[PDB]
Image (cartoon, helix red, strand yellow):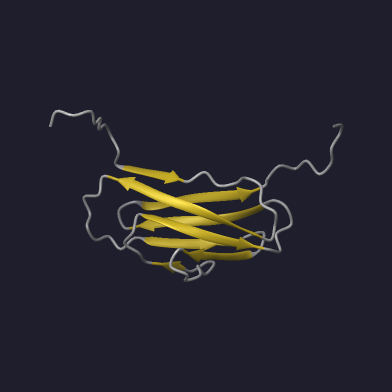
Length: 124
């Protein structure tokens, strides 16, 4: 009751572990998602829909199961780690994470890898 803890408005916050912006193609990065909501709903089932537009690789759950593009999975954990193993990615690839829910509707997160278009070095 009387301790240093400050609470103010946290209905739904999506916290992502800082991933490496640049990836070496054949490399594996871990995208750690932590969703910190109010959490009135004990059972909402939720929905995670992953889509792979450009690039190429497998986004695997911390469990091991691979996420199927365009398809979706149902879960209970709001905090989890994703392991994206890329390989045939050219340079700048985008992965689409559609967090879907009955009450939260839809929250789309796009993670672009590399992105930067500097193909040359004008001067070093």
